[PDB]
Amino acid sequence: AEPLKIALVETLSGPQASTGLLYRAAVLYQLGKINEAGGFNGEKIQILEYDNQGGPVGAADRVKAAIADGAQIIVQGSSSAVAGQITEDVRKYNLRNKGKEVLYLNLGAEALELTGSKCHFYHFRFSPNAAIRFKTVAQGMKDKGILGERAYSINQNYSWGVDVENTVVANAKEIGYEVVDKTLHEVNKIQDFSPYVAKIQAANVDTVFTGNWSNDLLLLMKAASGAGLKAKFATSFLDQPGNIGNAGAIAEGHIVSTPFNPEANGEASMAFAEDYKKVTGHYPSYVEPAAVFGLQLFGEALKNVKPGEGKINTTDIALAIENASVKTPMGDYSMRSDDHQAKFPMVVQEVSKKARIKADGTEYGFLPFKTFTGDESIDPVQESCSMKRP
Ligand SMILES: [K+]
Image 1 (cartoon, rainbow, N blue to C red):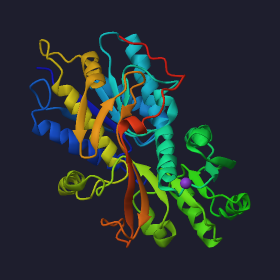
Image 2 (cartoon, rainbow, N blue to C red; image 1 turned 60 degrees about the vertical axis):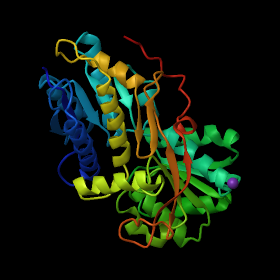
Image 3 (cartoon, rainbow, N blue to C red; image 1 turned 90 degrees about the vertical axis):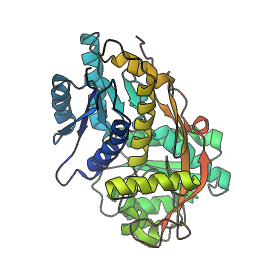
Image 4 (spheres, helix red, strand yellow; image 1 turned 180 degrees about the vertical axis):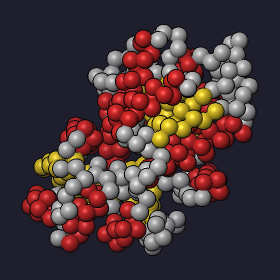
């Protein structure tokens, strides 16, 4: 029997590897569970790791190496720029090597193009995307009565920030808010956000939507606190590890929408968090739940694949993913065939002292206040995705 070989292509060493190493932990955790159940095709699944130190260009080289080493599946998630390279190199390879197609399981790259203008049959996204993040965070705040009528959009000036801005603008009419002004700023360089905060203060808004991460999120929220800006921040990345530890009371009351919260589904979500901590050493945070749950859906798909003469057929695997659904610790996970965007619940959360599980050793944690089903969470199919089918 031919074993299934899955290549993890991630930043796996050095000072920039924090997020890649969380993907590694989630991948080894859930592929470990699938191997505990017997693997695939009567053999354990082999996990091949490729440390990419070279960004998009390095990823092209590592994808070539993985395929040459016999991987039939590539997994990655820490960078949309790298994901855009992987998904196109995989698509191009597949077109030129009919019958030998490789799958790309995208476990966390959230740029809209991956299920839109770059969508294709051998890519599957198991994580949120910009539209899911910001439609659900806005709707959750609207439903709770804390959104207000006036909003500001502030994001980083690259593909991700543009996707977030476009989403926030597009949903204003339907959800019921006004985007008073919008700003795109330099990426991961600004130390003093006070001039941007002054503009937001002048706009007299209730809510600030931002897809910012790391310093661009934290230093912006801190400048807002120092200036007495009263608006709530509506974010996608407030729960990066360390953010609450570094912001403390400055983060209290601000909002994030994510696929998981350990308090959001009673014993099921707690038991998962404790099991994950037993295996990996930490509670599953940030990017890890979506990667685990996506690989849970993947494992369910494998269970439903019929083996033919012991050779692995990635087209059969892709069709099985389209058809699969699994109950995760957060509820039902399935896959949309039109664009291969996964359908799954989203939990809108507030930083609060009243959360039972604390973040970063502080008095604060993420308190869940609204859960949307997958049907309520998934974004509309983009007019730009036209997927050629086998
Ligand atoms: K409201």
